[PDB]
Structures are given as structure tokens and as C-alpha cells.
Length: 53
Ligand SMILES: [Fe+3]
Image 1 (cartoon, rainbow, N blue to C red):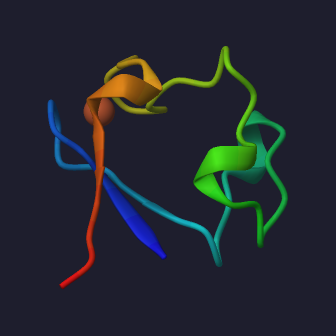
Image 2 (image 1 turned 180 degrees about the vertical axis):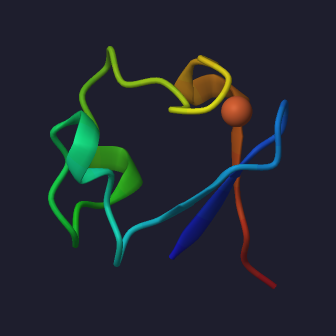
């Protein structure tokens, strides 16, 4: 699934992860460390919304 950062528009794609910040591809948003933040703007996880119909 994909989640959008409501502040800056960055999309966290679980298939892509965030390798440069220690997140391997396939890591679910709920599995992200509590201290993980948007890599673009710094926003906490609370500011993300799941993109699901
Ligand atoms: Fe952001």
C-alpha cells in the first residue's frame, strides 16, 4: 500500500521502502520505527494518510 505525507506530498510506497533511511523494501507503514519521519519534510507518521479507495 501507499501512504501520503499530508504536509509535502511524498508518497511512502511499501514496495519501495526507504533504504537510505534504513527501511528495506516491503516494510509496512505500521512496521516503521516510531521515530521514522517523512524523508522530505520531517513530518511524524501521524501526518500520513493511507491511499485506499
Ligand atoms: Fe512530508
